[PDB]
Length: 266
Ligand SMILES: [Ca+2]
Image 1 (cartoon, rainbow, N blue to C red):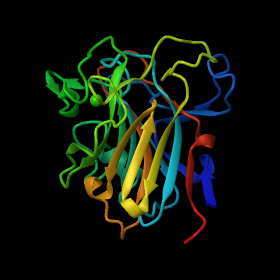
Image 2: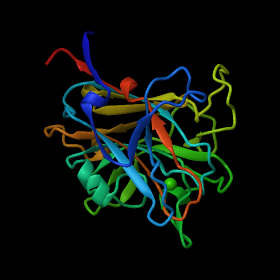
Image 3: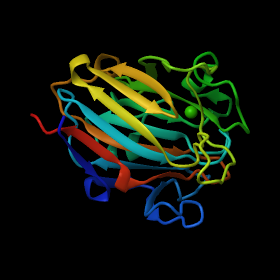
Image 4: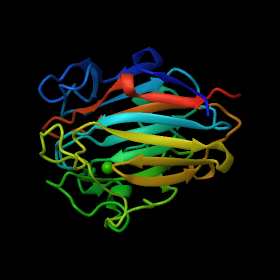
């Protein structure tokens, strides 16, 4: 099958807390990495998005690949995670309303999240984080989170949709160990603080998105996500760091290896 690919800073628009720089000792194999959440402010928290400049057409196949490197922080102090979000709205709306990583964000937004935080506002826990059976039971110092597709309702409220992870023995099923203390660049164990690909592979014939990350696979249909295949969508890569957290929540990608690949056929 012949495909076309767009990538890199020329094809994404930054919104909010996004910077670019080298990390020579920690990522000597890499060029310019793109960092979210570096504007640290425990009074407000922070957030950022990268918005793809072209529309997503859910009547045709696509594969989206995003290299991510997670903060090496426990789930009560680090960043909220990564939200790979499809929406009729834009990055400006996201800065205004929020995304898919918390309790509520942009109305009708949907997509895949890597949730790296146990979010608790004075004893009120984000609903999906409180799901000890499917999602999350290790809280505090653990660098433990979870993956899942999600859909924001007409009211913005985030709900879990699609399938639980399809190829795992982990308990909870959706678990992701998103970082550890390894600094070795060659070691072949999975290390979520190093760069690892998120792959979103959409099959138009079956209306199904497959998400692969950390060797785990999730699936959701356009019907699960509320996606109208007759309408073109925007795609955003999002991250955020909650207020009242007192160490860095820096989350990084390599934008020149963020690829949006589609058939050359119409
Ligand atoms: Ca969370």
